[PDB]
Image (spheres, rainbow, N blue to C red):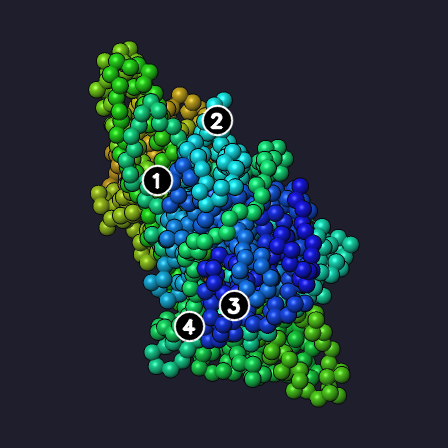
Amino acid sequence: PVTINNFNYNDPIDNNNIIMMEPPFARGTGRYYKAFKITDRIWIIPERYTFGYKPEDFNKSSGIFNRDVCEYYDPDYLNTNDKKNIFLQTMIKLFNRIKSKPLGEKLLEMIINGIPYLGDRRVPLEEFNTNIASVTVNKLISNPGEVERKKGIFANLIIFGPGPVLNENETIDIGIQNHFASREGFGGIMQMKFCPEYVSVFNNVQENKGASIFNRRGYFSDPALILMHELIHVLHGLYGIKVDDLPIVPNEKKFFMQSTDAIQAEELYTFGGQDPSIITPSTDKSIYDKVLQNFRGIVDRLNKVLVCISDPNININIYKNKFKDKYKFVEDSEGKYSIDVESFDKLYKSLMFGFTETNIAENYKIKTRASYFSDSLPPVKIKNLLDNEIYTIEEGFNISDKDMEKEYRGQNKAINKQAYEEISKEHLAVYKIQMCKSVGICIDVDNEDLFFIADKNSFSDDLSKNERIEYNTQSNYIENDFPINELILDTDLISKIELPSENTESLTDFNVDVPVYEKQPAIKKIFTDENTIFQYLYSQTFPLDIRDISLTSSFDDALLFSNKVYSFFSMDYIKTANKVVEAGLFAGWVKQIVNDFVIEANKSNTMDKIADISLIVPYIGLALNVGNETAKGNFENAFEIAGASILLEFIPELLIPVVGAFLLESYIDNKNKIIKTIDNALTKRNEKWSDMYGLIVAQWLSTVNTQFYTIKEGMYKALNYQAQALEEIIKYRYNIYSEKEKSNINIDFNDINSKLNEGINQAIDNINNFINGCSVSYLMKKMIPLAVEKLLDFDNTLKKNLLNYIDENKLYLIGSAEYEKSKVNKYLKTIMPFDLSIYTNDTILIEMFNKYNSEILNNIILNLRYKDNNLIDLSGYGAKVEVYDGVELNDKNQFKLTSSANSKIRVTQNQNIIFNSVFLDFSVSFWIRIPKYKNDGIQNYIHNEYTIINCMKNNSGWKISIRGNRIIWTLIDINGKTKSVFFEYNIREDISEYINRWFFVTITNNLNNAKIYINGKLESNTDIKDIREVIANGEIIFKLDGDIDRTQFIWMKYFSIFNTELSQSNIEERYKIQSYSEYLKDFWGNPLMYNKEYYMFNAGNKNSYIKLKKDSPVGEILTRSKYNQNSKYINYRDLYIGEKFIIRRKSNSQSINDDIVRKEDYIYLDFFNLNQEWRVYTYKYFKKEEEKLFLAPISDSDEFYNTIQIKEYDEQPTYSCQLLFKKDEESTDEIGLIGIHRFYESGIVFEEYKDYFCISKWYLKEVKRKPYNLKLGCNWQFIPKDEGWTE
Ligand SMILES: COc1cccc2c1C(=O)c1c(O)c3c(c(O)c1C2=O)C[C@@](O)(C(=O)CO)C[C@@H]3O[C@H]1C[C@H](N)[C@H](O)[C@H](C)O1
Ligand SMILES: [Zn+2]
C-alpha cells in the first residue's frame, strides 16, 4: 500500500525525510530548499517555483505568459512559515484523498516504483551512471552556513509551489544537451509547480449550472483531480514515454482564429474523453512505435549493463530486477531479458488510456470540463481545504451529509458558495485581441472566445506512403480505450520488487537545460472592418455608467450609440420593450414584455418540414452574423440552400491523402505464402479505410466541431445579453416611479428573472440540438464523401494490382488462381460503413451521431427544388443539375416535361455516397400530374410505353416509365435481370381521382420487395428476391422517351431520393407535409385562384352539376353528360359543363385581376349569365333548416346575404373545400353551408324529385364528425379549363 508521511514545516532537518535539497535547475549553486518526503521517492518543496522567472514577473503586469489562461497573480502566496505549513498539510490531505481509492493508490504506486533508469542516451549500454541531473539530486548534510558536506539521493517527483501564475499548474521534465530522458525510455526526475487553493472553473455547455443566468454559473475543480492530472504527466515522464510527435497546431492566419501553443498528443491522452480522437490513428501508431523502440534500447541495456562507475555501491542485480519489473520485460532461464508484446501492450495502454483525467474523474465521482478544448473561466479560491465540513478525503466537495453528492452539487458555484471566494479581477490578466476598425473604434475580445481551428499541418500524411505486403504483414489498431475495471483489479500491474535505497554518491555533473520564461503583451491590436460574431455580440452590451437604454433592430445604430442595444428578436418585441407606461399599467406591461421574450426565444423550436428540415433556429443569423453574412436576408432560406456550411466562420482545407500503393512481394512455388500475402493486402486495405475515417474524425473535431462550439457559446451569450437588457429597461422604468406608486405596483423581480431564465434554457436546448445536428451534417456530407472518393480510387488501383498479381503467379496457384480471383473482387466489393463510435466512445459525440442517423430526413441523397428559376439539389450532397431549355419551371416547384428533345434534366449523382448497401435499399418520392388521354388517340395511349426518368450505368439501374394509365418502376441488375412493379388507375370512371390531377408517388426497395405507394397508401408489391446487384448512382435523365404523341407532356414536383426504404408511416407523413398549404386547391390540385373561371364539382354528387334554371333565380342540379364515342377502353363524365363560376375577393379594392384564395377568406361566389356577371345569394329570413340559393344579378339588398367564407374542415389532404354563409365577418352566427337538397315536386302534370343548389344548417354539425365525411354534399371542387383534360 502507499504510506503518506506526516510533518510540520517547522520540524527539524534529519537529512533523511526532511532535508535541504538542491533542486536540479539550481545547477549546484544558490541556496537550498527545505524539502519534505511525503512518500517514498516523492518530495514536497513548499515554496514558489522561481526557476526561469524574473522576481517582478510575480506581480500582475500588462503581460501574460499563456495566451489561453485567465492568469491570477499574488506574490505573497507562501511568504510565511505558516503559509508553507498550510501548503504542506494540504498536499498531505490531497495525497490521502488520492489514495483513498484503488485507482489512485495504483497511480501513486506506479509513480513511486517507476524509478528513472540510471543514465540516459549518452550513457554506454554496459554502464549505469547515477551522476546526471535526471537521476540524482543532492541534500546538504552539513550544518547551516556552509555547503561543506552533501549526499546524493535518487528521486522520482519533486513538487514545488506555484510559479508566477498560481492557477497555471505544470509538470516539468529534465533536459540535458537538448535531450530528455523522460522522452526516450529512461524516465527522469520529474518536477511540478502546483497550487491547491486556486482552482479552475468550467461550465458545461449542453448542461445547466443551477439553471440560471442571474446567479453564479459553472463548477469549480476538485484540486485532487487537478493534482492527479499532473501526476499522470509524472507517470508518463517516469516511464520515459512522455514522447513528442506531430502536434495539433492552431491556424492563426485569420483574425478570428484562436492563437495558442502546439498541443502534443501526450496532453490529449492525459485528458482522455474525446480528446484522444483528435489524434489520428496514424499518429497514435507513430507514438506507439516510438515508445516501443525506446523500450527496446532499454531492454538491450539490461542485457549489457555490467557496472556503475558513478556509484560503487549500486547493486547491479537489484536494479536489473527493478527495471525488469518496471518495464514488464520478460526474463528467461538464463537471465536474457526480452520484450513481451502482450505485456508491453497492456502497460502502454494502461499508462496512456487507463490513467486519464476523464477516467479518474468518473471513478472518484468528480466533475470536470467536457473537453480539453473548452473556454477557460476565472479561477476561484477555495476557502479552506483543511475544513472537513467543506472538503473531505473521502468525497472532496461532494459530501453526502451536506447533500452535496448528487449532481456534483459541492462543486456547483451557485450552490456551494460557503466553499469558495471570487478573485479580485485587478489581479487577473488575459490575452485579448483588440479588434479595430480603419478609422477610431475598437472592441476587446479575449483570445479564449475566438475560434480554435486546427491547421492542416496538425495531421499526419502517413496514409500517402506505400506499404510492402508479405505473408507476414498483419493489421494494426490501437485502442484509445482501456477497461478501468481490470486496471483497478489488475494483480500484476503494481510491482512487488524491492525499491532500492535512495542514498547514493553526490551529483557532481550539474549540467542541465533550464527553461527561460517571459511575459508577452496581454493585448494584440489588429485591424478589420468585419462585423462578425464579436462585433454583433458587442452591439448587444452597454457601459456600466449607463442605466437608460432602448433596444434597436439596427446593428449600426447600436454600435454608434451607447444608449442603444441591439436585439435580434421581432420588431414587435422591440417596440413593446421600449414602450413607457403609467404606473397603473406597469405591472401589465411587465407580464406582457416578459411573456414576449419567452415567445421570441421559443422560436428556436421552429420547424421547416416542407423543406425537409425538422429544426431551425431562425434568429441565429441576426444574433451573431457568423459565417457567410448570415445576418442578411432570410436565414432559414439561406440555410435551406447551403445548409450548415453557412454557419462556419471558416471552411477548413482538409487533408485527404492519396492512399499509397501496395508493393506486393511474391514467393515462387509457395502456395501458402503467395496466398497469405493477398489476404493480408485485403485486411490491410481495411486498415486503410478505418485509418482514413479516423483521420477525418480528428479533423472534424478540431477544425469544424470547435467552430460550432464557439457558436453555441455565442448564442448563450446573445440570449443572455437580451435578458439583461430587458432587465435593465424594466429596472429603469420601475425606478422612474415614486415610492408611493412603487408600493402599489405589483412586481416580483425574482419571478421575472425566473421566467426569463427559463425561456433561455428552453432555447439553449434547441440551439444545442440544432447546432450538433449541423456539425454532424457537415461531417457526413462535406467530409466523409471527400474521403470515400479517395478510398474508392485506392480500391480500384488495388483491385488491378491484386488481379495482376494473382495473374503473374497463376502457375504457383494452379487450380485456385480463380477461387481467389473472385475472392479479391467480392472482398473489394463490400466497403466499410462509417461509424463514429469506432473512433471515440464519448457519450455526447455518440448520441449526436445516433440522433442524426435516426432522423429519416438525413437519408435524402437527392432533393430537387426550385430556386431563382432553376432546379437545384438541396440534399447537401451537391449533385450537378442540368436543366435544359425545353423544361418549364414555376415557383410552385412544378416542372413540365414535353415532347421536345430539349425538354430534359440531367442529374449527375454523387459517386461517394454509400448507396451500394449490398442488397438494394432506397426510396424515391415525387408528385406527378399525367394528362388525360386524347379520345381520338386512345389506341396509342394504351399501347405505347415511354420512359420519363431513366437512371442507368453499365446497362444496370432503375427506370420510371409510363404506358397510358399505368406508371411503372423497373429494376435491372448487373446480370440484365429485370423486375417491375406498377400502378394503374382506372380509365372508365365517371370521375377519376387521378387523371390529370396531382398525386403523390413513393417507391421503396428492400432486399425482398419493390413497393409502390400512391397518396400514402400501398398499392402494388413485387418480390425482387432474385434481382442481384443494381447500380443506382448512375446519371439520372428526366425526359419523355418513347413513341409519344407531340402533345404528350408530364408535370412533376418534389422529386427526391432516399438511400433507405421508407416505412408506410414516413410516407403517409411526407404526403401530409407536401400536401399542406394556406391556400385551397382546385380540382386538378393547383392553387385556387381569384378571378378565374371555374365549373363546379360536388364530391357528394359526383355526376351532378349546377345550371341556372330558365324561369327562376335558382340553380337546378342536372346529371353530367358522358363520353359519347364508342371505345370500350374509356368512360367519363364531362367536367366542362354547367355555369361558369368565378371567385371574387371581398376585401381591399386592389382591382379584379388575380390572386390566391386562402382558407377563411371572405368572398363573393359569382358566375356568368351570358354577357353579365351574377352572384350567389341566401335569403336572410328562412325559418326552415335549408332553402334554395338565390341566383341573380349583382346588387345590394338588405334582404340577402352575399358574403361567403371559404373553409376547409377536412384535416386530411383534399382538393374539396366548403362554402359557409355567416351573418357578417365578425359575427359568430352561422347561416349554413352551400350544398345540394332533393325536393319533392308534384305538379298537375309531373310528379318527381329534383335537386337544387342550396344552403343548409345541417352541415354545420356534420363537418365536425371524425373521420371527415368526404361524401358530404357540402364538399365542392373548382374545375378550370386545362390542356390536360379534353372532352
Ligand atoms: C332528421 O333530419 C333532419 C331534421 C331536421 C332538419 C333537417 C334534417 C335533415 O336530415 C337535413 C338534411 O339531410 C339536409 C339538409 C337539411 O337542411 C336538413 C335539415 O334541415 C340540407 C341539404 O338538403 C342541402 O341543400 C345542403 O346544401 C343536405 C341534406 O339533405 C339530404 C336529404 C334531402 N332530402 C336531399 O336528398 C339532399 C340532396 O340530401
Ligand atoms: Zn496536462
464 sits to left or right of 406? left
Res. 1254 in view: no
Q: Which mark is residue 335?
A: 2
Cβ–Cβ under 8 Å for marks 3 and 1: no
Cβ–Cβ under 8 Å for marks 4 and 1: no
Q: Cα distance, mark 2 to mark 4?
A: 59 Å
Q: Is residue 520 above or below residue 977?
A: below
- Residue pointed to by mark 3: 164
Q: Which mark is residue 1047?
A: none
Q: Which amino acid, by three-letter code, is at mark 3?
A: Pro
Q: Which amino acid, by three-letter code, is at mark 2?
A: Gly
Give me the residue at 49% from left, 82% from top. 562
- Decide which of 286, 519 is in the foreground and name it: 519
Give me the residue at 73% from left, 87% from top. 739
Q: Is residue 705 above or below residue 1045?
A: below
- Residue pointed to by mark 4: 521
The image shows residue 237 at horizontal and vertical percentages of 49, 48
- Residue pointed to by mark 1: 788
Give neighbour class at mark 1: few <14, some 14-19, many 20+ (Cα, 10 Å).
many
- Decide which of 1181, 20 is in the foreground and name it: 20
Give neighbour class at mark 3: few <14, some 14-19, many 20+ (Cα, 10 Å).
many
Mark with earlier residue (4, 1): 4
Q: Cα distance, mark 3 to mark 4?
A: 16 Å
Q: Which amino acid, by three-letter code, is at mark 1?
A: Val
- Decide which of 328, 27 is in the foreground and name it: 27
* Label 4 SS: strand
* Label 1 SS: helix
Q: Quadrant of the N terminus?
A: top right
Q: Cα distance, mark 3 to mark 2?
A: 50 Å
Q: Cα distance, mark 4 to mark 1?
A: 45 Å
